[PDB]
Structures are given as C-alpha cells and as structure tokens.
Length: 285
Length: 285
Ligand SMILES: Cc1cc(-c2ccccc2)[nH]n1
Ligand SMILES: Cc1cc(-c2ccccc2)[nH]n1
Image (cartoon, rainbow over all chains, first blue to last red; front, side, top):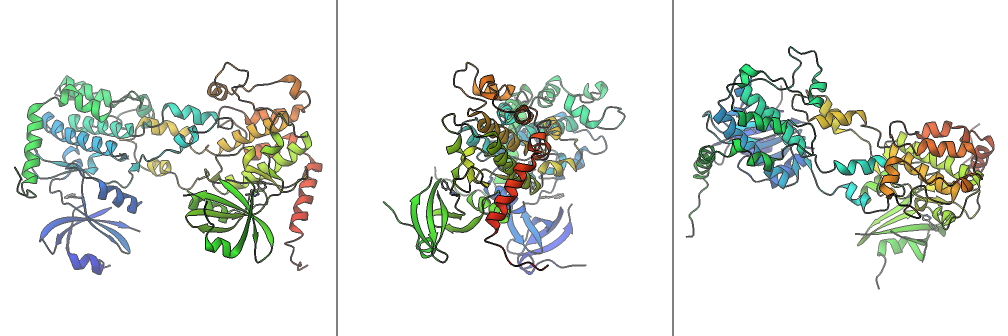
C-alpha cells in the first residue's frame, strides 16, 4: 500500500473515502469534519483561483499540501454530489431545480464577474450542503477553469494589420464569448434536473452526439416535459442556443420569469443565514 | 539621464544605438562586436525559446541581464534590417528575393518543426548579415511568439461531450492551423520584396484594410509585376490564400518551382561555410 505525508498527518486525522480521490478527515485543532482532495503527480493555478474567490455557492480551500501528491483541504458538503440525485432517470421537484439553479447562476455570475470560466460544469461538480432537499449548493472542481486576463488579440489589434492573417481579423467578432461555454453547461444541467434525462445522447438515436450538439437539436420527450412548466423549459431553450453571442448570459437567466420567484429567493436567504449563524460576530449598530 | 547595470558593464563596453532599443557593444573577453536589446520593465518565455533554438537563420542569445530593465545580448547583424532595403518603393532584385525568402522559409520551417509560431514576421524582424546583397539572413524578435505544447482541446475531447458547448466542437475543424499565420506574413513579406509596395494598404483605396485582408484581395499593379516572373507571383498567390487550411505550408513553399533553383541554393551553402569557417574544429576522417 502507501502513507499520508507527515505534515498532513500533523494537522488532520484521515478517514473514509467520499468519492480525483476525495477523503473525509478531521481537523485536529477544531475536531471538525473536512474533505481532502488527493491529486496524483495546473493544480497551483486551481489553488490560486480558489484562494481568491469568495462566494457562498463556490467551495473554499482551507489548506494545501504539495507532497508526493497534491492534497487540497476543502469544506465538507454532507449532501454529496448533485449527480447522485439525477442518476437513473431520477427527476428533481421543479421547485428544488429552481433553488439549486438560482445558486448555480449566482456562482457562475460571480466567476464571470471575476474573470473566471469554470469550463467543466456538470452534476458531479455541484455539491449539496445537507441531505435535506432545500439546501445550499456549491460549485467545485476548478481544475479545467481559465482566467480571462489580457488577450494577445487586444495587443495584436493595437498594431497595423499590414502583415496580419485574415483568420485573426475574423476571430475579432466572436472574441470574448468563451464564458458562454459555462451557460451552455448550465442549460444541459437544468435539462437533466427538470427531465431526469440528458438532452444530447447516443441512446435510442441514429444522429451522432456531435451532430446533435452542433445543430443544437435536443431530444424533446413531450410526456416527460408536460410535468414541467412552460417558463422552466423557455429558459432551457434560451441557454441551449447554438450561437454563443445570442446564448443567454447568467444576468439574462437571473432576469428570466422562471427565477422571478420570491418564495425560492426567501428559502435561499434563510439557508444562508442558517449557515452564517455560526460565523456571526456582534454588530456595531 | 541614467546608467547601465554593473553586471552588464563588467562584461561589455556599451556603444552607439543600432535601432525595443538595440545598442552596439563589445564583449571585453573577445573584443568582438555584439548587439544588446534593452526591454523596459513574456521576456523570460522569449529567452527560453531563443536558448533552445539552433538554426543559422534564427538569431542566437549570447547573454541575458535581469536588471531595472531586461538586457538581451544577441549576435550582431551588420547588414541591418531588411526593412531598410524595401522602404520608399525600393525593389529587391528577383534573385536577392529568392535567396532571402528561401532562408526565411528554412527558418520558419525549423520553428514549426520545433513547435514555435513567430506571430510577428515583418521586414523589421528579418536581419541581414552584411552590407553585401548576397548574404545570410536571420529571423529576430520572438517577443510575440507562441509554443504549440499540449492543447486543452485534446484534453476536452478525451471526455464525453454531454455538457460540451457546440462552438468547441466547431473549432475542432480549424484547430492546429495557427502556424499558418506565419505563412500569411511570409507571403506579405515576399510581395513587398518583389514589388516594392504592400499588398494591403489604405493608400489610394476606398476599401478598408480589414476588408482587403479578409477577402484576400491584394492590390495587383500589372506594370510593377511585369518585371517579376510568373513563378514568383504564383508562390505569393499560394501564400496569400484566405483559408488557413488551404494556405501553403513552409514545406509546400520550399517545394514550389520558384525555389527549385540550384544556383540560389549553392550561394546560400557558400555563405554558410564562409560564416562557419571561423567555428571550424578539425575533422576525424
Ligand atoms: C470537495 C468536497 C467533496 C465532498 C463530498 C462529500 C460527501 C460525498 C461526496 C462528496 N464535500 N466536499
Ligand atoms: C539583434 C540585432 C540587431 C542588429 C542590427 C544591427 C545593425 C542595424 C540594425 C540592427 N543586429 N542584431
């Protein structure tokens, strides 16, 4: 077999596997439960992003160990992955979909505002805070995430194009819509949550999965969707748009009539203050 | 005014400006002339590329100083920039064009073979070895150059595209033709050398420089080009192709009938052994 590093061991009492390998552990100082993600020897860039982000719907780094393997100490999410709530045609309640999606939009909006594109949004990277259906969700796994920074295209455009290739000038029209990939993913997530099935699949189809996606022709099953509201499906349709320039942004999605739900918003604010009740320092007044 | 760093000063006797600021200097050890490029405080990446490249038509780093400014010690090219031979409608002899272009193709072929895209090829970055028209040329300024490495697209394609945005699947067709930007630039260079004028310009034209380039509709002046061979112009036409997938590669260009010139090839081999006569260590036999 093999051992954990002395420095990890010094600080945490390592326990059972949760689900990259993720294990349960206990901070010795606090006796509190943590999740430790092991990555066998991009991880530095992931730590750099996660250290600077600060949102209740984005996972927080608690510690990091650069040993024979990387060890990332994260906050423990007792509800597990959202994937385990959607597998085997399991259909989430329309209201539960909204509460979770609203949080995913808030998290992805924060990311975009801060110049971060996740690039790998799926149910397996959306964690639930408790075994309760009305709970806080957090976006995890920033391993494939990208930083928007300062484009080499903006620098190239400052010059004279005497020697500039045409394809570079053609890319100017689309440039800066990479974040739209995160809205596609959210749309595929919302579809799976609402219906219990994926929009693009090789199951009972002749058309290749690639052709389905490029044509943006999702598998629509009327019997399944008759249970879902017209508003929920309208948002799906608006995110599953092929043109990344026309596709709905996180701001447009958050403005959609489906998310204009004062009850759902109240429940989220309530879950937030319930979580925050622990951190609560006395107020000035 | 201001001073040079003690470490630079220790090794070189700094002299007159040559032309980023480039100054003449003398290595104290050898009493030999060098060119020192000063960059005021990407430069590390430029040094990393230039340290690993090894071709007679690519400039070599001799030293580097990371001071209040960057100081890059390069080999001195007495012929200066090719730009100074093409300004003010100055037309290079068809044979001189070939000798220089053949070397530019050999240099750019080496770059591509080694996973480097220059991204800023122009007459001002092509240096001449002597004041003689039959001379060795060297490609300089790797400041905007890029490394091909390991694409995130190849990593993304290893997964299932259930959640993958359509535009990512659409980019798969063009992916890996970025090097073709270097062949466009060479084509714009060859045109300027042969004709004395640029193919795409705002001078005596209604059509925007952008529109000219995307349509690939170069300004063709028959009287000017009647002096130039049909073969020379055929190669230009093959490099000034809008589709980066159809555009001529450095290998295709080097195979073109215009470069199938045994005389031109002989003269280059002769200039090479003339340069190499100094470095010459005794042979084993
Ligand atoms: C980063 C992380 C992973 C987890 C987790 C907890 C239980 C089951 C599955 C996953 N919490 N936090
Ligand atoms: C890198 C470099 C620059 C030069 C140079 C020499 C004379 C005139 C203009 C430029 N040689 N090498």
